Length: 178
Ligand SMILES: [Zn+2]
Ligand SMILES: [Zn+2]
Ligand SMILES: [Zn+2]
Image 1 (cartoon, protein in one colour):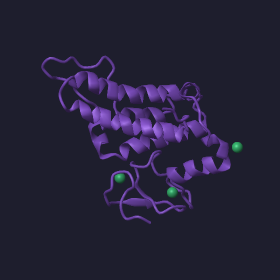
Image 2 (cartoon, rainbow, N blue to C red):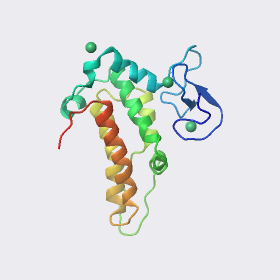
Image 3 (cartoon, protein in one colour):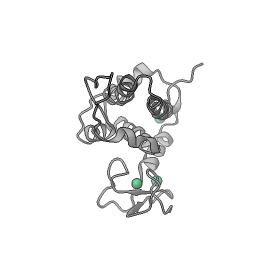
Image 4 (tube, rainbow, N blue to C red):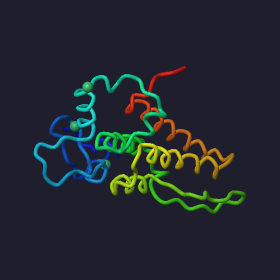
């Protein structure tokens, strides 16, 4: 197994996957690493199994159909993995915890949003369709772009949004286009 967490790239108290060489901090894995379960299989392994059981699940899909899917267990897992892929980028630190807004010339968003809030919402099964989760994720970056206006710090929102969108297209097998 690896000697650093796959998500945050630090050592510490790590739980090892039984079916691949990745390791995790307890609350770095999503969902949080399970208390028992020997052997234990990480989210990466669980996602790979879904694709292996249904190879046609990788044929292209329309985003509009994906968003209307109900959050059954396989879609719940996919959204957990997509959230985890965002946390894997170190620039996700900027969007993880609850923001506050006091900048001359800007007003805070009407509906603040952050990664840990999305994480809680997934854990608590508050999203009934994929659309719920994707809307809150995109709102994180939209709020950031609007607030920071012409400051160069707006670029961090563009950067982390790009990681979200690339992973969304991969995990949900969105049809490739020009
Ligand atoms: Zn970690
Ligand atoms: Zn694994
Ligand atoms: Zn199949």
